Length: 53
Ligand SMILES: [Zn+2]
Ligand SMILES: [Zn+2]
Image (cartoon, rainbow, N blue to C red):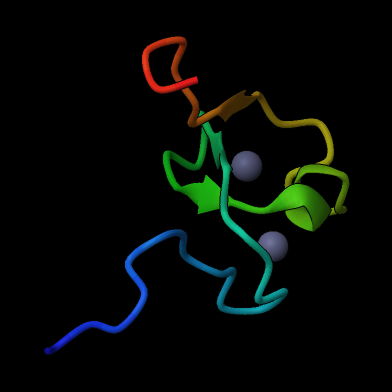
């Protein structure tokens, strides 16, 4: 089909499993970004929920 493995995305720069999400920028980020100059002092929040796991 159109998609192959619909599991998780990957940063367009780090290509890492995107699980985090910045608040200010209002966009998705990765483990790296979180601890990067770009979103260093930014409010990053996890995109996980107590529902699934
Ligand atoms: Zn990243
Ligand atoms: Zn940010």
